[PDB]
Figure 1 (cartoon, rainbow, N blue to C red):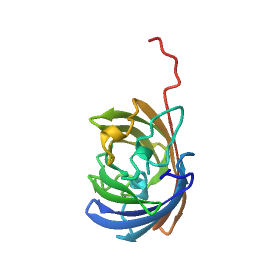
Figure 2: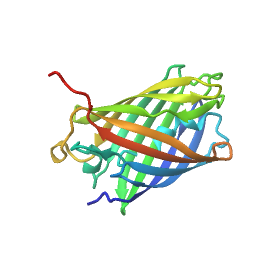
Figure 3: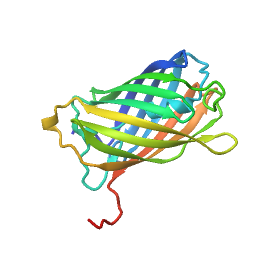
Length: 223
């Protein structure tokens, strides 16, 4: 098929967080059907970045989720045209990060294009203070909405000193393949484990790995 057991990817990212512009590029490889993937990320403009690289990690790949049981894989269905996604992350201490993304497929390579706009990050919060230690695992919940696919997500950011800063994100996944040509799934969930493998030089270069596994709810029903 167009999606192979081993796929490579390229990323152009750019945007602004609390009036600080920046551009990043990434390179990576994953096993889309195993749901694993690596991203090696250079910051190429705006460095040194005043905020924690932790707020951009969900912005660097839906093609790498292992849809177990028989869950219709929205993301792999829409190639050869590809998909898009739009996200609003809201931190409980005010920070708000809107990311816009385009996923494309040209010459067997997945090209990601990303537009970030972060606002209201507090000067004295652990994000702008760079007091964060990556993310906890989380269950994302997905569902169809108006020919689209909605993702709902609570994530937990480790803090220096201990404890957590929670955020919430709303994601709309939109196919570029027309409705009639893909089989939408119902309600289901994706268990995620986003992780930092490496950073060099004040988060100037960052390596990221993900496990995404889709499933139904295992629990017994009385209905």
